[PDB]
Amino acid sequence: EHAKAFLGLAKCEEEVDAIEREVELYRLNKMKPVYEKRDAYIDEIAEFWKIVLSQHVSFANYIRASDFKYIDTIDKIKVEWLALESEMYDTRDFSITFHFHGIEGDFKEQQVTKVFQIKKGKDDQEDGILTSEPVPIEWPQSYDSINPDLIKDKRSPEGKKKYRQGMKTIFGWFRWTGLKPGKEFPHGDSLASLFSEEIYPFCVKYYAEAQRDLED
Amino acid sequence: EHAKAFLGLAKCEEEVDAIEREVELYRLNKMKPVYEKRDAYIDEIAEFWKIVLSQHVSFANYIRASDFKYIDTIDKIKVEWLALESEMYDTRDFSITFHFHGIEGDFKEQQVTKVFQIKKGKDDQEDGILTSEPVPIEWPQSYDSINPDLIKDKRSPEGKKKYRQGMKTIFGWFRWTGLKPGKEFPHGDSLASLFSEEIYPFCVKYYAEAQRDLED
Amino acid sequence: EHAKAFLGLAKCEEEVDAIEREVELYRLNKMKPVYEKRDAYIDEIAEFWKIVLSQHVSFANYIRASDFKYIDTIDKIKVEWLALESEMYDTRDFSITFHFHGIEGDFKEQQVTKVFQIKKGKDDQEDGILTSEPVPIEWPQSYDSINPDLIKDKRSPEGKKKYRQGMKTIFGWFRWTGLKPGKEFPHGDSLASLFSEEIYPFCVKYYAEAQRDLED
Amino acid sequence: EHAKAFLGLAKCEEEVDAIEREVELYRLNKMKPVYEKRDAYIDEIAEFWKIVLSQHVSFANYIRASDFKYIDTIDKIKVEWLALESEMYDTRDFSITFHFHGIEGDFKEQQVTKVFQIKKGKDDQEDGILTSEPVPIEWPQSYDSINPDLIKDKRSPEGKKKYRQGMKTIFGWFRWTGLKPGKEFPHGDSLASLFSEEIYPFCVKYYAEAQRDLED
């Protein structure tokens, strides 16, 4: 009845995995209402996101300094976890919504939402990896020369170069999917994790740290 | 009403911290019953712990190979989380219970339990650190020469050396407290964490890995 | 006897330290002529440095992406080791010389050299740490608002902020000394090491890697 | 022109590689005589190696604490670099010689030397990796049950287990070659590097540190 034991143990492991999911759902449910309250207070501080995003340590490593002109117009960010809507979603799946104030003559005021979900390929310990769907955004006027929608050739030496430059901008990240390795915005996956795991949850601590450095 | 906002945010952080604790209690409560069931099956495999303990990668780094003779007689381990009994305990606080089969003429069959709880010293980010109380154990006959209870001098060059050698054995770990840095069993705290965070929860995975290496 | 031995060993360590210096001098002397030859070939490839600097992995982490506009105009870099000129210099001491092509009406074409030398503070094991002297540079026109030489106040909340922003640019690095911890360009020392230990010696390997990726 | 330049740079890299070898030979030649002098003084301190080997931080991670009984009898270690004898040897190639005092009726007093040399497999960047030849050693009497030369079966479940246990002892390391990955003493290569790069060169610093702790 070592047999019975082994069979029993295998089933217990499965129950452990089920428990971890139940625990995570509990956490996400309880946190949802507090995030909504927090977000409401955030809306009362006009320059909040601009400050936080410029303060983060590694965020800046992902995007050309050129983009910051536009990143500075972000005045709202909201993350929502998809597993709260349906149990068919992995606990790590989420949507992220940005609002931009825009810039006269260059960049339209607009709201955009992107969705990220996990998938597995089997083969290798792989807990599974993030994927996303491209989502439309109206690019800044000045980015017309590296806009993939305006470049006619993108197959010529010059066109190919312009194309790759655009895909390396923040706007190229919006059409990231994780399904064409080496052909999309680099590390779109790690950027997404930065948001769900660091930036959205601890933004206030980042803001405080930034306002602290104003004094010394 | 940035003021109101800031005050509101500070309170929300506090609620976050409360939620994390509530989440942890939920996890520990749900897991308790599964651990009891698992443990029951473990009891049916006589050499389980001996195998697991010899299999772990880093456990061996903590104790003289000499001790393994006695570690091999362990036939039962149980961890219990104190926060389940009272909310005055930190979520990380726990008791650990060992049973030894013993060895004829050298080591008595016996059961011992040690308790670990967190404390903070303030000063430094310190999430707080583990502490424990010494607990009595009957040492193996052959360890008489480095037994702190039998060494008369322990202040002479020879006595001091014998004393330090005994405190570096597994049995010296049992009187570890974490309150006399540099004078007790080295890294008693990290060893304790090995048990609560790795060895007890994932013992089955370690056992399987060990039985897997039997084949190649 | 044991005495004699210990004195002998102490002297041998001293001889080891002397040998390490002798070995380093040999390396630097033999390398000097090859660097000069190599540099001559480098001068024939106009966009060399621009490409290499944009290619390095961690260089970008040190400076605002804004600065790259100007970093891209660097068309010459030369490192020389001061220990070759005098034995009073530590083997690690060096001068670094930059030439910038400039940008009409924003940034003047110019050549600048900075010197770095080791010093010790004693106590802490410290092999000793880098120091430098501030060296004058004509800042880009567009950097006028965060130029420490043009800010009148720099003590008001706005002036202090503008001042700190300028000191965090590449140009602020040029007045780094390592003598006012926390008040100068962050990690000026690690940046200097990047140049002497990685960028200058292995630039060609970085360039190749960059040209390798340009098609992919 | 550009052609000429590229050919010139390729040749300069080759010269760099040649220089590194020349520098290394210089270092090894100058150090040889100091090591001989130092070793002579080391021979006058009977318990030197025992203390040093028990003191090293990570050495212990490689071998069963059981082996220390025998490691404690080492009273002499000598490393020599083969590149000093012939230029056909890589700078990293070396021989290592141990002398053991032995233990009456368990372990014979004896001297053993092993040789390590680099080889390349091509493709993977591989600077090339260490290889060695098995060298005969008379095993301790008590290790008879896991001695590969005494196990008759080593193909039965018990024999296979005994065999693998022996190959994981320090004595199994002596027949390591690096030519049968996963079937020989684990990480024999990293252990060899520990000796040539850390233990032999800095033994004195380790000894001092150990004598420093002996009072604390």
Image: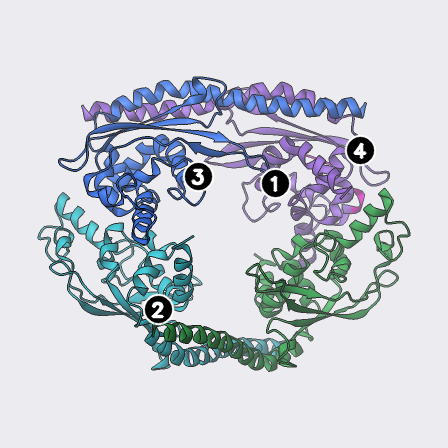
Chain colours: A purple, B blue, C green, D cyan
Establish if A109 lies above or below C122: above
Establish if C97 lies above or below B128: below
First along the sequence among labels 1 and 3: 3
Say whether residue A68 is visible.
Answer: yes
Residue B2 located left or right of residue A164 = right
Q: Residues within 10 Å of mark 4 (few under 14, many from 20)?
A: some
Q: Nearer the viewer, residue B175 or C153?
A: B175
Which residue in the structure is indicated by mark 2? D119
Report helix, strand or loop for mark 4. loop
Residue D122 located left or right of residue B212 = right
- Callout 3 amino acid: Glu
- Callout 4 amino acid: His
Residue D109 located left or right of residue C63 = left
Closer to the eye: label 2 or 4:
2
Report helix, strand or loop for mark 3. loop
Which residue in the structure is indicated by mark 1? A191
The magenta segment? A135-142
Q: Residues within 10 Å of mark 2 (few under 14, many from 20)?
A: some
Specify whether disc 1 shares its chain with disc 3.
yes
